[PDB]
Image (cartoon, rainbow, N blue to C red; front, side):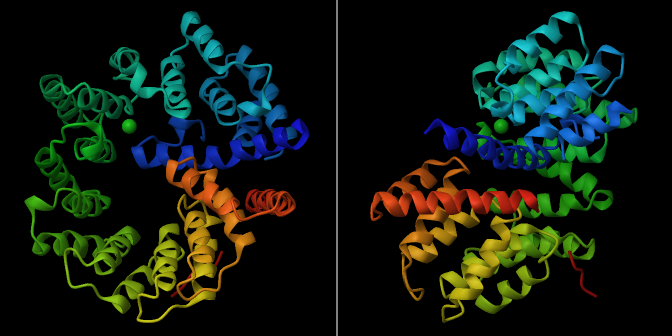
Length: 395
Ligand SMILES: [Cl-]
């Protein structure tokens, strides 16, 4: 039935677009850089708002303002196509972006880079990235992050030192902010990108933390990932600096420490205490509080709390909560099993697109009859709809 399958696809663009935003933000991209900043204002508001009517109203509103020399319309349009392709059968984003590059539009290369990042082909075009970004570097500060990424994957130490000096030189001249430097540093401290320059990442971070406090968290997180160049003494210092600056993520990582007890003696109620303070400021809090209640870590197991907090996180964009809610309903260990919910949530976790999620979704659909599967699939979409359709503060 290509009727619903083509409905499930449009709702899959929706969860995938949210994840792409979160990953671009984590990486350092500003809202301007990801296309979130008359027909111009409107067509842009709509594209990043939405129903398939708004996606199409957005396209046209943008496509027009474009022809009429309205800057800040190309990135917004490219994101629309890249984030909801199943809403645009008429378009082939890559060709569209290839046209704009040929035309000479300044923001084309950036659009082209957002392309490799959204579709997942980055590693195949490190050369094209390098080229696009060397040319836009003095006009698009996010390119410092992309070149540092390239020089990390291409394992090119020399080019990185030149880049870093260009970046420092720009700090001196006032053309580079502390957030860029922080982002570049986190690139240098990414064991995933190849051969990390952790110490350089540290030198960079320490200079900027006093005035860009999110760096205390980056520093703490940098020790966690390279445990061998700082003591619990430091860790706890960077974290204190973080707590003092009012950085909710400081509470988050601190509670994670007492949760895995690999840096300090595993302590159950302390972590809950710490994660609790990030609740409402960091979606992961709800997720880490959900695990504790699922694994019964506080000596005992609390089913309804675990679901409650795990669902909240899943409904707020947490890419791992649905997977967990699946495990909660299947592994027993305190929680009575429920095959249907297990399925529905392992299917929702599939949308996050991970082998782990695939591997779990096939095991949990195995127990269902063809009717239950169609029922559960009915629930999957009902639930995705609700998320799309969607506060209170303490003190
Ligand atoms: Cl990457």
